[PDB]
Amino acid sequence: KQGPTSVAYVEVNNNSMLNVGKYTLADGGGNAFDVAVIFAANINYDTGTKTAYLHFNENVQRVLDNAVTQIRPLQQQGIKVLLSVLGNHQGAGFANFPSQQAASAFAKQLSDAVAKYGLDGVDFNDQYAEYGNNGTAQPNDSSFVHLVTALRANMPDKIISLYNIGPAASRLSYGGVDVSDKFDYAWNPYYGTWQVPGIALPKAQLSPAAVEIGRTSRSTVADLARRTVDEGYGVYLTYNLDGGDRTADVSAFTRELYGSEAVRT
Image 1 (cartoon, rainbow, N blue to C red):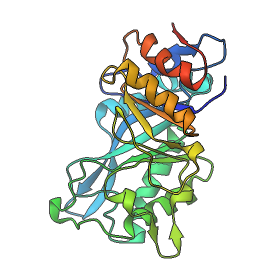
Image 2: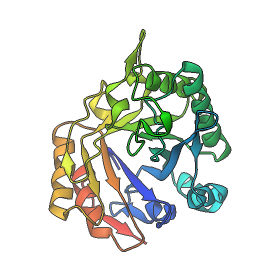
Image 3: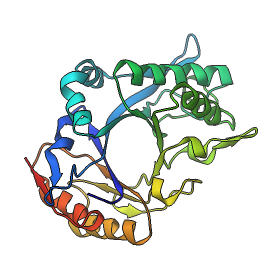
Image 4: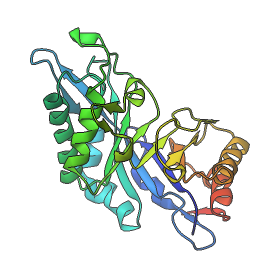
């Protein structure tokens, strides 16, 4: 098929990753979803060592431990799988590292995770960090740049994206480096709306539309998908695909982006 790249966030905790691959286009043209994102790992803080670390809840860990059965089937059919990282009420956040060296240590935990679990990239979602907690600093200018710069250096052939939200999103330049061009995609964080991300990426790699499967209206889902193509954008963010028969929500958007309706297994 041909059109904008559609993404699906899956809440590992309650929902199967495997559900993304159950949707294909009726025109015999391909997966309805191109990117699948594991929601989500976290940025935690160790107050004794004053060091943030990449935290995985047991349920997210389990998906990763069983990557062979839970993630491999999607990559087999061509769906790229990213791991998303969210703040976790612990002060430490992406725009919070006190030194290049500290951000790069977290960058390393990120690259190594993608490497070990054979993922295709990382996604940054700067929400719920609660900067200030645990004696942490408020957002600084350099922090996010350091982290992205280093992660990008770590995995040059992998995907790095972000939700256009939180402190980090407005802190993309520090020193001679603007890290916008190191991201593959950027998306609107408000499901049910159209908000063009104000970051320096081609329209082909920006998703102004963000929808929640099962919460967003099917007319809104159709409308944001029609507007994505009409405005010349190349990404369509979808969120919270579950295990129920969602063929119509999916067709609602596939017919606008791809000119085809979708069929689920």
